Amino acid sequence: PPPVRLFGVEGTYATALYQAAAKNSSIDAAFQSLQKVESTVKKNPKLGHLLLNPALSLKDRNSVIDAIVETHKNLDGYVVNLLKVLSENNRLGCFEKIASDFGVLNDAHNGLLKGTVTSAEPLDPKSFKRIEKALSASKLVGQGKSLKLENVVKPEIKGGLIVELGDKTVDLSISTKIQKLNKVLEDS
Amino acid sequence: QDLYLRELKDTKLAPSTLQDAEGNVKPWNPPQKPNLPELELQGPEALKAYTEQNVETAHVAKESEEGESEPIEEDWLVLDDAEETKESH
Image (tube, rainbow over all chains, first blue to last red; front, top):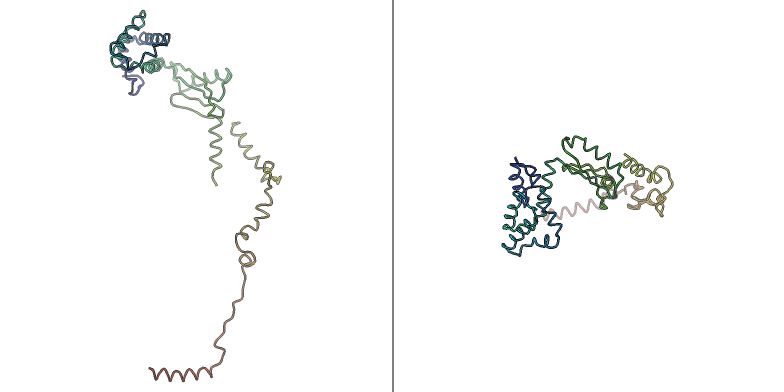
């Protein structure tokens, strides 16, 4: 019984890392180790990201893994061997993707159903809050699970708002309605 | 839905000064009245012919006659030429 699929390409490292780690939980600890190692990649951005290049070596890649485990107890559990394999497999560059994806799987386990409330201009907090609770208590979320929510600014839309989550959306905005306004009048 | 309602009310109203109340058309600088109901009211008869095609010309048939009611100087020549054709028959 796997979680929500990462669907093949290069999430399969993260997929195997989860489903082999999770057989004995520790995925919060493995998760925090992943957060910490992506942090120390980010905390040393010069040649933490600039040294995920493929043209180095096998040996020097393994030594960069040694520098990662050299930084205190940055790695913990399977995630070093993960890197041992990753280093050997030289898929280190697509490591950022793995991180974010494990985060998605993890907060799916928590049930944070990330949403969005697209607009062409940011809005007041009262609207945020009222919408937030709306979806939260809506059949969408079955409760027992959270509900983030992000307003974004979109100029490509002419205003209004659109709610999004669980590949399920509602647009009541302006742009689409103008469109429907032009379509209906486009007949004889 | 104030989106829907205000869009549809402007949608009805800004041409309602063009169709319901004859106040020409505020945004259009050329007028709308001397085009279709005045100039091209004769439109299809500017697209067809006036005063013969559209008035349709209820015309009396030009009366052709019989062979001028003269059956002497031609029937006897027909009978003589028929003697000739029977001499050819």
